[PDB]
Amino acid sequence: KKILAINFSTASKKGEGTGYAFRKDGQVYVGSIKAYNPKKTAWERTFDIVNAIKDIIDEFDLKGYHLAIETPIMGRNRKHSITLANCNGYFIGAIDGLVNGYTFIDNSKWCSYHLISGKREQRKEESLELLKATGLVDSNCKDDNIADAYNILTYCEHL
Amino acid sequence: MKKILAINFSTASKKGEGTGYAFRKDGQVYVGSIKAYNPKKTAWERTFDIVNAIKDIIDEFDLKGYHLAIETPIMGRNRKHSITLANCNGYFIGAIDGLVNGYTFIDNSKWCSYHLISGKREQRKEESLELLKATGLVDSNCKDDNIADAYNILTYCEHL
């Protein structure tokens, strides 16, 4: 029930990032770690993303939170998919112990509970629509990493 | 001699298989395998057990600051199996990075090529074990190819 929700990406494309969401003293906090940098490898960007999340964990002194992280999946691009799966694992291994374990949340599953339907690109705008309603972000927000992490948290808080 | 902890990572999905490790300390090579076979556990749960076993080795033998050399995960025939394997390999590395001074991926092809090992998987296991057996660290009857691959990664990395 004390859940740190993560939508993990290594930010291999511009503007991407790892989204996070959690609730502390009833207040929801959300954000993204924007790590795009072609001078760094996926694993180096991952290291930076780990250290950003560790800094939030210490700032908000999250003790006993459980990681809910979106399951890595094989996509069309095989090498991207294996790199992402490996970096997703690095991220989980680096923070497990700061969190009390973790659970894989299947994209299809949180999406179905929130009625997000259609392809990938369209899921992104549906997820953002839900984030926008809560007014934790402004009406201009185009951060689907943030929106996904939020929707994963709400999925988990129900399940 | 650069201080390297060589790992041949496996989730021990098959009985008798496990994660191989090799390191040199005070000139002596130490090798072994973590035999984590347990079909009652998921691959991630066996990986957690292997992480704890390597942390205990790093503690007992005072290896903080050794550099981790680990095989690169590869693309395979079955999507879900290869994604799970790649994720567990990642988990292992992220759990111990910090105890070790960083890590480097070692491609299977590169260490094999250095050691003049060719052929399909089972032949490569045989040739890798021949190199390990020659050191006397295991007996002439050893079939523990996870130990052999860890050893042969260590010696490949020691030449670089």
Image (tube, coloured by chain):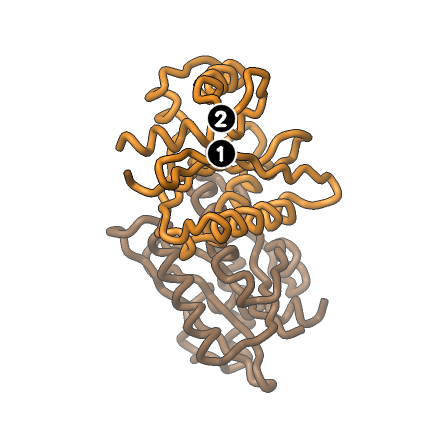
Chain colours: A brown, B orange
**Type of amino acid under label 2:** Leu
Please tell me whether residue A14 is drawn above or below residue B147 in the rendered image.
below
Observer-side mark, 2 or 1, equals: 2
Q: Is mark 2 in CB contact (under 8 Å) with mark 1?
A: yes
User: Who comes first in sequence, dot 2 or dot 1?
Assistant: 1
Whether residue A88 appears in this view of the structure is no
Q: What SS does tag 1 mark? A: strand
* Front residue of this view, candidates A7 and B74: B74
Residue on which disc 1 sits: B31
Residue beneath the point at 51% across and 68% down = A147
Figure quadrant of the C terminus of chain B: top left
Q: Residue at x 60, y 50 (%)?
A: B48
Please name the residue shown 47% across and 41% down the image. Answer: A82
Looking at the rendering, which quadrant does residue B158 occupy?
A: top left
* Residue under numbered circle 2: B137
**Circle 1: residue type:** Val
Chain letter of mark 1 equals B
Q: For mark 2, does the 10 Å Cα neighbourhood hold few (<14), some (14 to 19), or many (20 or more) residues? A: some
